[PDB]
Image 1 (spheres, rainbow, N blue to C red):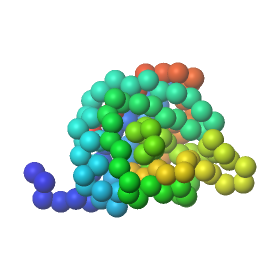
Image 2: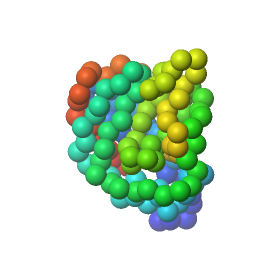
Image 3: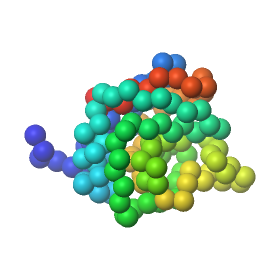
Length: 131
């Protein structure tokens, strides 16, 4: 009941795909509180080149962490916009590498799943829930 820290995993299912992701305080225990606060909730998924970002109505913004580079397989939350986004390929600016944004936090990565959600259908439901 709150006797740890590096063990905060959430669930994110899709009408045509499913995947799990964990999280580490590297971003900030304070912000992590909002994500956990936004358990089972309805959200609309927006399709984008090997990228997916949906709003959950949770407005959590602060100046900290905000990274812009990451390796294939890791997951991150879009700070400027309070929107979460998966990573399994290109992004708004593929070119030679993968640029998810200019200031997004690393909310962990996809381990027990390795699903290819990136192949989601244009516009589909989304329900965020912490396990």
